[PDB]
Image (tube, rainbow, N blue to C red):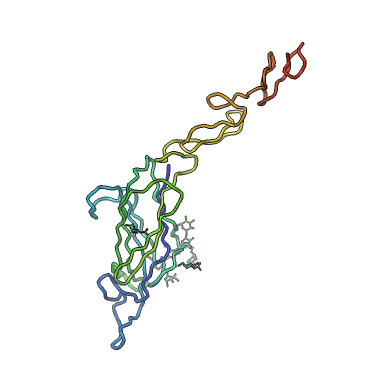
Length: 231
Ligand SMILES: *[C@@H]1O[C@H](CO[C@@H]2O[C@@H](C)[C@@H](O)[C@@H](O)[C@@H]2O)[C@@H](O[C@@H]2O[C@H](CO)[C@@H](O[C@@H]3O[C@H](CO[C@H]4O[C@H](CO)[C@@H](O)[C@H](O)[C@@H]4O)[C@@H](O)[C@H](O[C@H]4O[C@H](CO)[C@@H](O)[C@H](O)[C@@H]4O)[C@@H]3O)[C@H](O)[C@H]2NC(C)=O)[C@H](O)[C@H]1NC(C)=O
Ligand SMILES: *[C@@H]1O[C@H](CO)[C@@H](O)[C@H](O)[C@H]1NC(C)=O
Ligand SMILES: *[C@@H]1O[C@H](CO)[C@@H](O)[C@H](O)[C@H]1NC(C)=O
């Protein structure tokens, strides 16, 4: 029943700097001002319900996903390393139409000779708005003092799930137990020449006494009756 997909595209940070202005590696050079060491960037994505108080201490009701080190400084996210893009937060209820989202870009060292790593928060963004179920991506781009993160987000229903909250189930069928498709809200729209609850009954031709339907618009005659309509 539906899923919220957040697809990260590009994180920009050519200077390898921090939320507080300093550099992630912590060492520059005397002249100029550029730094040395780059910024090993991970991400944390928290999706929660719209709770109308814009607070960050509440629980991530949908998910609290942590990303491995994807790149250094500026990163082109639009691969693997165990990470899936887009990130999917599934649900089993009606989509509430509203949501709250936290996305953090983090620095994190990764030297195999250390028993403890060094982490620095690079950027934090909050997205809390009303979102409708649609196959179109909504693209945004958050820009801080040094860093920029571009992403797409949307909610789409799972397979065989129609409706506005992705709750009404419907599967097309074309066998002895039904011949039909589904509409936009999830109603069983039947193929031409079918009828009934699941539309397992064919529709014969104009007339047909004694004759019956094995397939739509046809009539099989019984003993003692000929013609087209099996009169
Ligand atoms: C911190 O560093 C860790 C080590 O990385 C090293 O450091 C730097 C210098 C890198 O440039 C790199 O070159 C170094 O190796 C790093 O650990 C790595 O973590 C990832 C995910 O957390 C692991 O990925 C998994 O890999 C296997 C297969 O990988 C093979 O190929 C690679 C190269 O292509 C080799 O390096 C490996 O040794 C293997 O030979 C995948 O199969 C697996 O996907 C599976 O996911 C689930 C299981 O969880 C299954 O259900 C799926 O079906 C898949 O089978 C992952 O993609 C990677 O192995 C690991 N490296 C090593 C050496 O163990 C870590 O990510 C860095 N960051 C953090 C935050 O820790
Ligand atoms: C890198 O991202 C840009 C979008 O900013 C895209 O045009 C390009 O295709 C990406 N790189 C590759 C190798 O596709
Ligand atoms: C991007 O930022 C917020 C949504 O996070 C919204 O107020 C703004 O209008 C968005 N702009 C575009 C062009 O999507």
